[PDB]
Image 1 (spheres, rainbow over the protein chains, first blue to last red):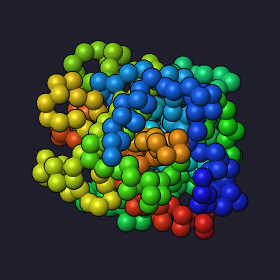
Image 2: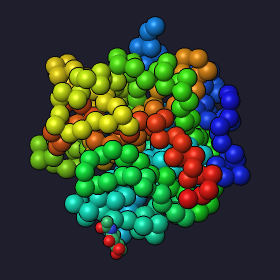
Image 3: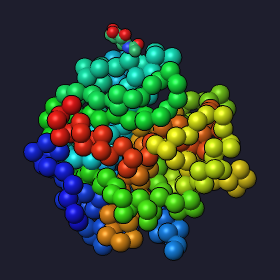
Image 4: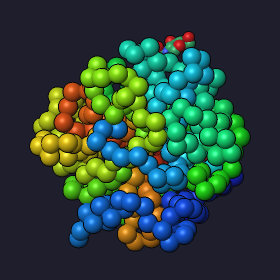
Length: 42
Length: 258
Ligand SMILES: *[C@@H]1O[C@H](CO)[C@@H](O)[C@H](O)[C@H]1NC(C)=O
């Protein structure tokens, strides 16, 4: 993940953003992610 | 949020509740982009016509929540604001163009299984995901339906709501409203038929419109709920602040700290 901000001004969190602890981190998928990924057709 | 469903715990760890101090009341939705910065809509902070002109002291934010009312001890965190930055070109007297605001927290919020920032998009993410037909997700605590159509306690959700919405063709929404849709916004919603059409409501304003990248598995906030067409508002599609187009401004503010 290519970082964009500086943590001295932006605070912590950017490097690990968007990855949910109870989902992506546990290899678990939420109830409807499917609907979203299924719509990103070429 | 209309025609949506209850949120699973931690499904949107970046969801933020913009609260009013006194009287205590949920005001808008918002999102966590870092442990010190929060994104929400400008009309949520400043909009004289609905008697809204708040300042750092007037409100606070609740993070890590699920329940709309019940205090969730050892999970939610309350934070005072240090400063509010509403886009200088936001003009409440004209339209919703550049309807965006950055909120700085007084104290960094500690992360947990229920508190985690969402990602801001890059040009690459926008060109691959922000396109008509692709679906995104909106979360919030706004009303479930039109007011007056039943007891209020039955239209205000008890738990956070979620709904998936398709991005609408720009020409198609420009033709559905007399409101101007600038290049700094995009529309989302189901077609005029699909009977039970999901959407965001007033209490959802300021909330995030997210999309999950099939390329790196991360969630990106593509938009900020500016004007949902759900509940009491006239209209077919919701308007969203095109977050990427305002990224430079976000950076300018953060670099300098406003
Ligand atoms: C907001 O209220 C302040 C503080 O009283 C006042 O100076 C300002 O005119 C108000 N904002 C607008 C644009 O109405």
